[PDB]
RNA sequence: CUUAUGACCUGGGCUACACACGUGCUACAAUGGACAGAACAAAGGGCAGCGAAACCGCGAGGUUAAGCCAAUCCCACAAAUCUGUUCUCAGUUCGGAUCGCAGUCUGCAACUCGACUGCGUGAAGCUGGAAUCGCUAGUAAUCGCGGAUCAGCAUGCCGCG
């Protein structure tokens, strides 16, 4: 898929894109505005042009693949450095 | 083809000259690739045995075997002769096509693929995996995919040492 | 090869969104793909985006 | 503090400057848990008064983004 | 009791929870969720205080500053509600708690220790056991508004519609 994760085919593009971690409401709407799709369309009914548009937009922007690692790195850092905040994190 | 000529013309001569073998066919060769499914979850889902059998036929036309328990176990609620997992042996153009498909789609399709395990060399010269996702490459029909458990793949080579097997795999394109 | 126990193998042209074409004997007559080997950044050597974002923190002393 | 600048106590900053002008040396005791960690704090094994004792803590690079109280617990159990 | 059961100061605790129970708020959705347009308020406060208007910023808010010791000016464009677009019965376009990051109000400093905003997720939860509570008219239910305590802190209090 666009971000390597399947999206609902029977839903609007706006909310279909939200199922990707890191890409929420504002990010999805901004990507749709950049792509020029009007935000009212089915994802099962699209063409290669606007598909590749969103694909390259996502590849240029941040993705779950990077966020999953960045958040984990930050968490491990703030846990290892002491950081009573990090202590609470480890405690859960 | 697209792999046999590449091998015979780049991997064999280069590796032979690199390792200073005393004969032409002394170069290590990939004998076969065995794919296994491992599951005894069939105990709780008798139809689970059907799963990964229709998927394996699409992954490779070679129909898998319904391997059966060679020994019973109470901890797993097992009895000798009950079906557990599936087996497939690719030898010939099938293994070449499987390697091509894998390298071209499966590894690049994985979301978080980076620096595959270096550990999973046998010591002996074989290389061993358990893909944990059942929808790695396109022939698995994401829509029809219901269960998510991937496949064991076992690469077997005539290499006498792990070092030469590593070199062969890297020259073939294994992104270590 | 047994008779009829296996599906018919067919040569197909594996396609990619970036334009790379690969050929492999597959059940499907054609296979559409989005990320091929070269398309995946790991195969592109040191990826630009990753090599650019992989820098360590500097305490954010810009301000 | 958002744009007024980072935060630190004057006496603690003067102590750290005196200790860093020549070479990092023995612990710098202080009761200023409020102070925020700066790059200058690196290498100095500062001590924090948790209420009944001083806990010496070696401030590494990544500590700049936290306060001394984050490393000076107070409650007991 | 008294060179201490009195007094000064830094920090901590008063805010810890395998727990149980009173009171209140939010939820489990189609009388609904999100977006576009529109109307009506009643009471109270303002001098180191209240602060129009303009600009900046998605935002909480920041800068210049009019006016007001007040039936003048401001706080302060009430929301429910209505007319439309849209989704569709699902742990969901329900709920936003816990949560990571980035910021805003204040203040020497929100780290033990406020609130608020954006980002990305999102569970518990789909009506809840004995039993129990308030309510006879502008009452019940329910939607907003202002003040006390206050540098900065309200689901509680006082009242108003």
Image (cartoon, rainbow, N blue to C red):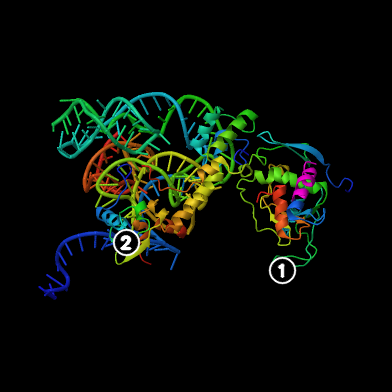
| Residue D48: mark in rendering | 2
Comparing B43 with B135, the one in front is B135
Disc 1 from disc 2: Cα separation: 59 Å
Q: Position of residue B27 (x, y in %)?
A: 79, 54
Comparing B149 with D11, the one in front is D11
Name the residue at the right extreme: C3
Report if residue B9 lies within the magenta region.
yes
Q: Position of residue E85 (x, y in %)?
A: 53, 26
What secondary structure is found at the residue carrying circle 1? Answer: loop
Q: Residues within 10 Å of mark 1 (few under 14, many from 20)?
A: few
- Residue at the (72%, 56%) spot, across then down: B164
Which range of residues does the magenta coloring cover?
Answer: B1-14
Which one is in front in this view, the residue at disc 1 or the one at disc 2?
2
Query: Disc 1 designates what residue?
Result: B74
Comparing B72 with C34, the one in front is C34
Relative to E20, E65 lies left or right: left
- Residue at the (78%, 49%) spot, across then down: B12
């Amino acid at each position: 898929r666009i971000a390597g994760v399947d999206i609902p085919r029977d839903k609007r593009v706006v909310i279909s894109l939200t199922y990707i971690f890191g890409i929420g409401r504002t990010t999805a709407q901004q990507v749709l505005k950049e792509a020029g799709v009007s935000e009212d369309t089915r994802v099962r009914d699209l063409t290669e042009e606007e598909l590749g548009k969103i694909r390259d937009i996502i590849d240029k922007l941040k993705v779950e693949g990077d966020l999953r690692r960045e958040v984990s790195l930050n968490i491990k850092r703030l846990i290892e450095i002491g950081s009573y905040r990090g202590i609470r994190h480890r405690r859960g | 083809n697209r792999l046999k000529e590449k091998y015979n013309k780049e991997i064999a001569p280069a590796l032979m000259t690199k390792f200073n073998y005393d004969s032409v066919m002394q170069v290590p060769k990939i004998e076969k690739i065995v794919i296994n499914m491992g599951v005894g979850d069939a105990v709780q889902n008798a139809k689970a045995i059907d799963s990964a059998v229709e998927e394996l036929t699409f992954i490779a036309g070679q129909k898998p075997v319904v391997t059966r328990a060679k020994k019973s176990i109470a901890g797993f609620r097992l009895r000798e002769g009950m079906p557990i997992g599936a087996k497939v042996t690719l030898r010939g153009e099938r293994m070449y096509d499987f390697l091509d498909k894998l390298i071209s789609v499966s590894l690049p399709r994985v979301r978080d693929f980076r620096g595959v395990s270096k550990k999973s060399f046998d010591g002996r010269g074989n290389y061993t995996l358990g893909i944990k996702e059942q929808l790695i490459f396109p022939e698995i029909d994401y829509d029809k995919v219901t269960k998510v458990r991937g496949m064991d793949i076992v690469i077997v080579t005539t290499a006498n040492t792990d070092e030469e097997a590593r070199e062969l795999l890297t020259q073939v394109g294994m992104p270590f | 090869m047994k008779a009829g126990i296996h599906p018919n193998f067919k040569k197909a042209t594996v396609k990619c969104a970036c334009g790379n074409e690969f050929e492999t004997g597959s059940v499907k007559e054609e296979v559409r793909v989005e990320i091929c080997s070269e398309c995946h950044p790991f195969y592109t050597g040191r990826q630009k985006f990753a090599s650019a974002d992989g820098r360590v923190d500097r305490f954010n002393k810009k301000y | 503090s958002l744009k007024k600048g980072p935060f630190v106590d004057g006496h603690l900053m003067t102590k750290i400057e005196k200790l860093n002008e020549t070479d990092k040396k023995q612990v710098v005791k202080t009761w200023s848990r409020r102070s925020t960690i700066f790059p200058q704090f690196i290498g100095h094994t500062i001590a924090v008064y948790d209420g009944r004792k001083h806990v010496p803590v070696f401030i590494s690079e990544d500590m700049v983004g936290h306060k001394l109280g984050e490393f000076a617990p107070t409650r007991t159990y």
